[PDB]
Length: 50
Length: 529
Length: 50
Image 1: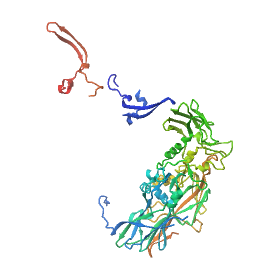
Image 2: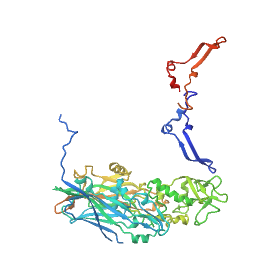
Image 3: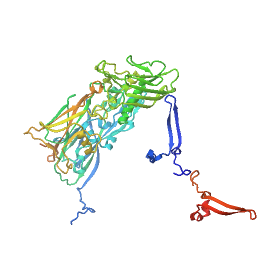
Image 4: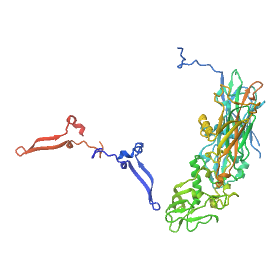
């Protein structure tokens, strides 16, 4: 809400991302993920981000 | 305002009694059906209820794949009868006993439901132990259990006999062809023990009671009709269908073992199909019948199978090897150039990774349309005379992993009783129509009222409390001819080119008759007229 | 309280500082000051800053 204060960043809620790239399907197949996402984030409407 | 006190009670002093747990060993007699008899004669046992049957399953040694069906304790029971000197007091079939206990999760668990009993275990050497000895407990729910001591069976100085008839051991065992079932069957013997709660009552004051006894009628193969005669006071009526696998060898492609969800059945089936569906090989794969159509997967990963596009992408394929797709793994059709049932066309996306160390494809995500009916097709039906194709194009290796399954309590046409094959039901009391329906609203009602998940189509005529009232029944009118219940159904129409169309069906009608229980000159029951 | 979040900085509460340097006393004599200091800041104990 303020230009140079606290920010809510969905990227900072991840701590470890591991996986394997697939050459055949040209995708990353993710294995273990360490994160702090909770139910409120899944419940945010897309309109409220913008 | 005279107010009823809802903060205090006047405690009644009950009849003086003492309960005791009592175990009995039986007398076993024997295609030689095994029968256990238990004799209860004890002057100080005034009443009893809560019968539990103990069964010791032995150690299973040898080679092959072996497992027990879920709820093996219930499924080994063919018939239970309680008798006195005046005749049978109460009896039931194993199917109906299991039906009455289907909502008791604790009882189902005690009768043998675990990974140790129900996984399909593998024996590698003739001395390998496939299963360890174990004991299961079967709660034989009787009408004498509903209201504890109020509904108990009183032994009016009479000798009570409990007789248990057992199913053959092939009914409770899931096995492959590699297991030596002939020797296992020659050696297996049921070792039963009977337990009950007895009551030593001081100055018991006995009154006559009422009891409901199930009566079961099975229709002839594929007939849409069945009738129960001599109906004078029924409290309920239930109707369901059973599959008749007698025209088959009872062999199926997969079984999920201890996992018993529909998703689990489908996953086991897909897992068994993937080893022959997608092949990573050096040149055209070998070892498949001549009717097999193995095509190479192009650079875009899409194979077309007559209006169907399968997307195959495998990682880490060696440079000397290619990816192949089986386009007609299982095929069925009745006319030569018409519609075909092809298990390969039910897949849309197959991805995985090849393992150089184990020389296998480890599959990751699969997109498919396999349902429970496919997992429920018998292997004999893929290769029946009516199939104009070679139905089974699997490898010999996967053909050798089919399982014999002889479970006696299967309803419907699939393992889960998920598809309803009854599109219309009509019941007649005499000649008049008593009930009619097209959807399964009576099954919805049975499940809602009994708080069950596996209800059947049921007409219940009794809504009064159990033992403190005389039950409400539909009463016969022999003058008007209303003394029999006739059931006619219309089966759901299946496609003639689906193999499940040729599974044979029987209609089962169960009727609960009302009996009076009197206690002069021992115990006796009389059918209410 | 957190390393990379909001900070309370007494310096950011000033907007305009004017004055004149004195060569004789070697001090800055301040004239007009524009600020947002309130009574709570004058009431903070020095121990609470550290």
